[PDB]
Image 1 (cartoon, helix red, strand yellow):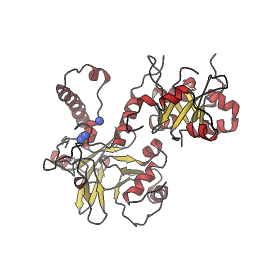
Image 2 (tube, each protein chain N blue to C red):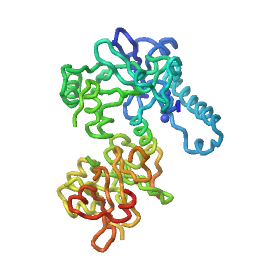
Image 3 (tube, rainbow over the protein chains, first blue to last red):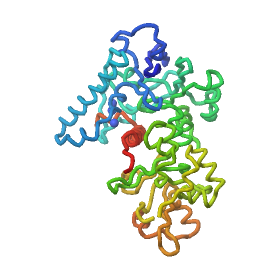
Image 4 (cartoon, rainbow over the protein chains, first blue to last red):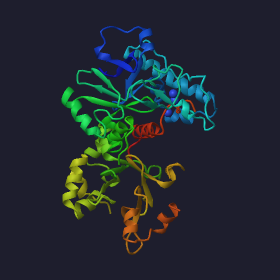
Length: 386
Length: 28
Ligand SMILES: [N+]
Ligand SMILES: [N+]
Ligand SMILES: [N+]
């Protein structure tokens, strides 16, 4: 068990809070203390979830989901399933106040989209401006819907909390600068969490592994600021049964799930026939052998930066199966029919290339290059983007 | 939608990928 697997947060003031990490508690909190605190649970990457969200983040097993059709007993059984995971987890962590705090504020009525009216979706701080939230809970503090923007957790597991404001000591300064001054003050092993509108405190490095500059975007936004990229390598985790392609950033995988069987196979040089690597120009994906061959210097730099062994570039089998278009959407590329209607010269769109004979080369190239070189899209690509 | 409506659209995409990637079987 991790010594920082929970943090207990308490209100001590107008817009003032204090936290204590599990390992720093000087006493064994009673069930009342547990139930009166905002309880933050550490997930597998060091994000911290308040209770109603930690509970729903328990996922249902594939088999159980399938076996379940019903409905509403559907909700009942999902809840009973998560309730036992939740209860057993609280027992092991030694927590005796196990309230979930999912109860909604029943004085608040939704708009026709079943969402909060704009007048009901803000909390007002005394000194720091307003903050937008996702949901109105009957127990707002305990549900996590009242925390500050920033949680710092030092190498000693001490918690410091912070609010941004328009024109503060970091106005128009970058998250990375705040970050450097934090690790100078506290130690370079210090963790920084940035609050989501939901109440989740996402670790700053988790956010950057999701999209470079996300941590900074979230940081700026707290102060009312606004400021202005394919993954380096990707692995196909789809094509199953055969199922659709789904290419997941290698960096994401290796940073965030260092003991995944995908991650560990990749580290040993396996699954190289499912790996795509970005050209020096940023516009094209190709196999690792193709890149090794066509640009050995960039190959060696990309593979060291991303954490893959250079042996992948001396491998080859004896490409028509691959999707005609892939689309970047976070740290993964998706086939067009996998994106929701709201998701869909986009610089996020990559086309399965074809040579002068009409045959698939295996590469994917950005649509912007098709426009710049005045190259017509292949017809398979062209109809998916219609 | 009370199981998911306390989450941001982005928090749900994050979770979806984490779950996908935690439960994905190696190829044969
Ligand atoms: N969820
Ligand atoms: N919730
Ligand atoms: N929720």
